[PDB]
Length: 16
Length: 16
Length: 16
Image (cartoon, rainbow over all chains, first blue to last red; front, top):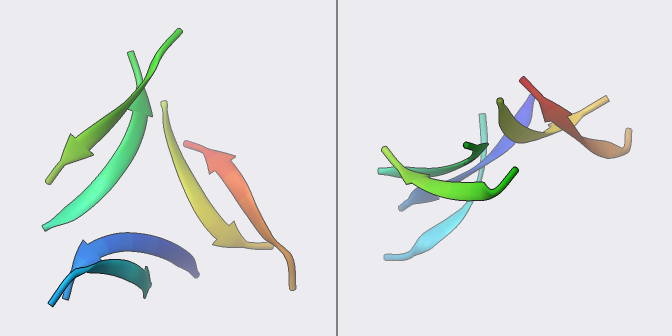
């Protein structure tokens, strides 16, 4: 998978 | 939302 | 195209 930068607070790396 | 980095060259941050 | 940081393990930028 990939690292998306998404709001989750703050914008963080998110594994998608 | 998530930040995507795409070229138009120049890279741009795309807000989605 | 858009650049994604994806596992390929090492995480590599892919330009989709």
